[PDB]
Image (tube, rainbow, N blue to C red; front, side, top):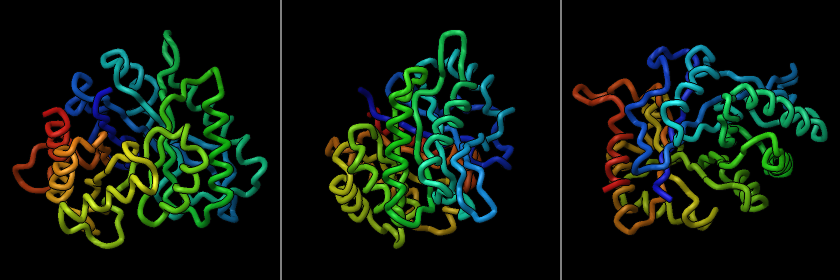
Length: 289
């Protein structure tokens, strides 16, 4: 329908800035709103190779099943998706056994997903693939492809929205996956804060975006921004250029939506006088108007 708005949450397990899912950014009247809950992370053997057995790594007191139930009781139109992988160098995609990885991943993720249920059914609407560190195109595209297929085919689940989260440095591996499974992947969430060289103008932004649509597919790419201080320090893109660049896209009716990296980091103003969620609220204003 509507412009898509997605926000990562739960990804800073040591942060105490939030004690529940924020309602300030929730807008289901003019936008299609998604919370991306993560990280479901695999256990690794001593060799640094992944087992495919996922566990929740977010705070379950703050964002667990009872909090998801409450959110959905109050705002039924919000979609909740689980993100798997992780950003550390300590959570790479590197399966120890290629023919057993997929069965462990399907079973362990289904177990997690089944915890997020109410009297009327499952509360999870999809999955997000967010492995930052992937060394080669393969077995990634084959194994991730099979996992998506198995989850979408399970009638016990409602895995309706599938997304991937590439960055400039891992984009080639995600492109391999996207080409093979184009029909099951709804959204490509590309993080502009992870570019190698700085994005200096709104024209440089626009030019990057168009090339992403060629690499993936027109209207399936959602530009993203990071309010995380680790990313702010890298200074690959400023909020002024991000807003400017998105404005240009909105003017030619070419922006399908946006995503933000992360609710914990956006609640705390960076410049005195800044309101909490200033970048998110500014993008919501431009997506409606």
